[PDB]
Structure formats: C-alpha cells, structure tokens
Image 1 (cartoon, rainbow over the protein chains, first blue to last red):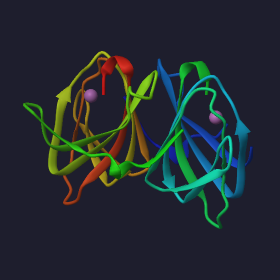
Image 2 (tube, rainbow over the protein chains, first blue to last red):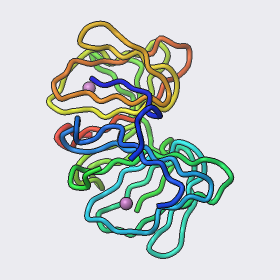
Image 3 (cartoon, each protein chain N blue to C red):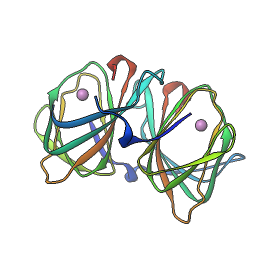
Image 4 (spheres, helix red, strand yellow):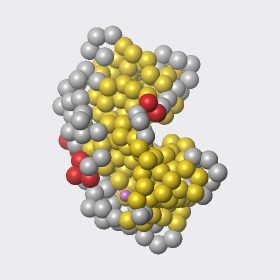
Length: 108
Length: 114
Ligand SMILES: [Os+3]
Ligand SMILES: [Os+3]
C-alpha cells in the first residue's frame, strides 16, 4: 500500500501541472492523475481512443465540448467516453484542480 | 460526456458484518465506464470498513477529513489531499475516528463490480 500527499508528486496545454499520482509503474489497469490549471490555463480540445473519469476538486472548470462549453465546479464528476471531443479551460482568477483517471491504454 | 454533481447520486447505506456507518455512491459505473468504476464513500463518525482483501486493486483519493487507514499491520492516518494505492489481495480497512463525516473517492477495475 502507498499512502502519500498528492502535491508532493513531481509533475510531468498551457498553464497546467499534470501529476501522475498512481501510474502504471504501480497499478495494473488504470492511472490516477492530478491536474492543476492556473488562472487562464488551457487543455486544448482533443480526441483519444480511451475514456476519462474526472472529479473536480477545486474551483470552476470550463469544459470544452464538441460544440460549445459548460462550466462545472468542485464536487462535479465528469465521464468522457472514448473518442469524444473534450478540452478544459480556467476562465477564473483562481487555481482549478481536478483528478483525472484513464485506462492503461492511455499510458499516463 | 456526463457532467454531474457527485452528491446528487443517491448514496446507499452499506451494512455488513465488516462494514458499519458507511454510505456509498457509484458516480461512474459500468453503465457507462468500460474499464473501471468511480465510487464516493462517506464514513460517519465511528464508522468502520474492517480489514478485508479482494483480488483487485483500489485507487483512492481523500476528499474530506482525516481517514484512519487499517494496514496489514497497524494503522496510519491520512487526510484530504492524500491518495492511496492498494495492491490486489492486500489487507486493508478504513476507520473514522473523528467527529465529522469523512469522504473519499475509491476506484476499482470492472472485475470488482461497483
Ligand atoms: Os483527454
Ligand atoms: Os477493499
């Protein structure tokens, strides 16, 4: 068993930190990442052939969709099916943070 | 794409010979997810998920409060902002020794169900 404070993980888009908290180094099936998006930060719209499972931990996250956008806040979860267009933007003055998990096929 | 408030998922009371004072939400389940499941557990004050093991891993992120982790031997406390990886078939359990509810995310691969 591994027990650790997330922020202590060294990080691996604009104005992002990406931490792989539980990577395939340790885990057999899926990966736990922590994303910190600075004010004005951006993860461009993209597509990958694997799903995302996300939990918004802090702040107000703009979710970029195939068409248009939606804003969610801390305490929201997000499921993105494989190949669905998605991106993320921080349109606030405050740090945004979210947990993001992907299956092994997505690497880290 | 699904975007929803976690708390809006109806929590189910979990009550077994080895679990007391616990509620569980399945946030992203096998209805939607092809590979692994996102749960949110709420442990009331004094609540207990006693030591057990399963042939699948857990990936945990603590959302709220101080979580006492029962390890193969002894215990260790973590808090909001900690993650936990539990290997398959490793003994583990959880206890809430505080006076307020503790919450954590807990993800398992599909072979573990929901
Ligand atoms: Os993506
Ligand atoms: Os378990």
